Image: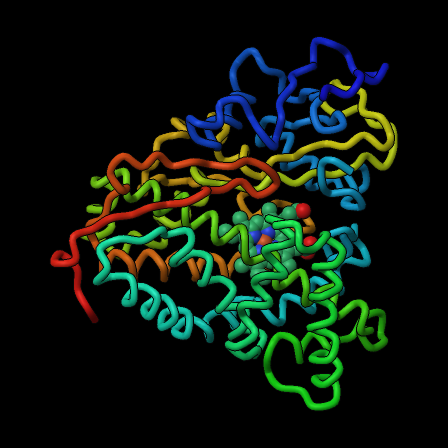
Length: 400
Ligand code: HEM
């Protein structure tokens, strides 16, 4: 339950927050985490839950620790104490792999994919529209990012069910496979494809990764499968759950929907403000050595949770942080991270979000939560929404 308190940790800093089941959960997950920002709570606290670990609670500390990779290492980035690249790597060896992955998901690739993204969104929406109802999480959000990966990687549609099953087992195991079995089966899938695309390449993400250079020499197969694996999984649960938080807010607030219906030009700014208010990731780092940080003695090997979610919710970074305002003049957040591991998919994610909102608001402008339905959130490394039953009158919609 509560791991015993290490000798170096003073008791006045103890705040037993459980990141997998925070106590205010039913009130909404972002609200449950923001208890860590109440005035009686120090900037840096120790929890005894989950093996015992630090938590930085304020934007200033979160950013600084992500900048200081010499003390705060990525060798162990999850609480509690997996071989994807470049997750576990600190600079300077991380730079090269990062440069390569950037070629496959960087801005020019995204600008090129933009209308394929739009057509996929339009066909999913068109199929739901006449029904007058859906579970948004299951019916739109889940099928969407996986299909964008198949486009990017030039993989055939028929492989989706099996691939989706494997990535589902890594994050929501049904018991059929351990984490390691699901990973190996994913590697079983990618290896022949990588091998073939070394010999005969295309312009897709797997071809580009497979023919890349590391340390002046060819990328190996081990390295290429471990990067392709991260490119797959990094863009699934984050996009599924983020779209859900956003659609939940818009379903509950007719006045914000209306604003975007009337001024669709505001949608890119609205996306940015939604990313701040409904931020959802909480990664960590491990201490490389003894280190005093903002008056607190940290010990070598200590783990520290640095919740990306909390920077944009900090009232010291944004005034009235729980209020959604699409006209904010300075939206400040670390929703996609900060420092050397800043999300490589951030440009693709923004386009997936913007396109989704533009297409949904055009075709189904008026929607609500299903009557009687109560929306359940879940908390962890990637917080999320269990399910999102939506309802609308089909007569108020339009086929395009
Ligand atoms: C709403 C959507 C997303 C959010 C909130 C998000 C969040 C994050 C965060 C916080 C990190 C850095 C964590 C750390 O510093 O340890 C990260 C890294 C990463 N993300 Fe995302 N992400 C999103 C979408 C995507 C997408 C669509 C992709 C596409 C494949 C992707 C691929 C990656 C990769 C490869 C990294 C590793 C960066 C590195 O270590 O160099 N992400 N993301």
